[PDB]
Amino acid sequence: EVVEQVKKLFTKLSSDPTTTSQLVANEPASFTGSEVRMIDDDLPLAQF
Amino acid sequence: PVKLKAVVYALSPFQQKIMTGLWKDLPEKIHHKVSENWISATLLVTPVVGTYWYAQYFKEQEKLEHRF
Image (cartoon, rainbow over all chains, first blue to last red; front, top):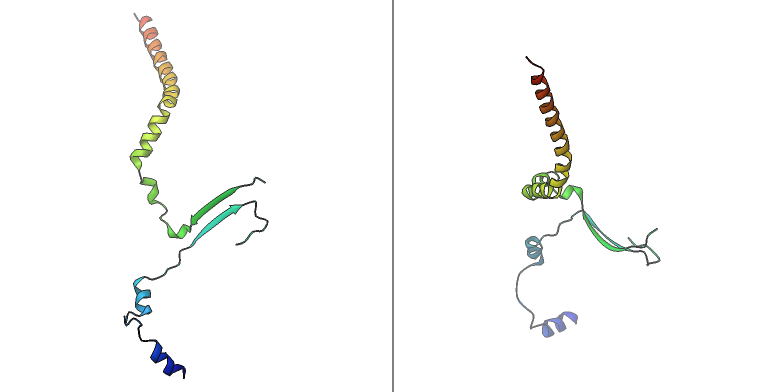
């Protein structure tokens, strides 16, 4: 019942075949060792 | 303890070049060293060099005068 309803209602979707694997390989993510320290002595607790 | 409000971003020592900064902007470094310290270098070198040359001039004249 779900499948028959889906193929009837979802008919205006984009047909662009660009996979997310291709997008990831085109804009890869890398890890950079670094740090950001937001010093605020007015905060009661430290969160890191 | 001093209350401080600040944001600090730091990069890993293994993600940056270590030695090439020694010879970067060398003309600026030399210009800053010369322009800020030429009075200081003058005040140290001139009395030493001037006194040294005067003593040698004094010795030369005294030596020549005692000759025959």
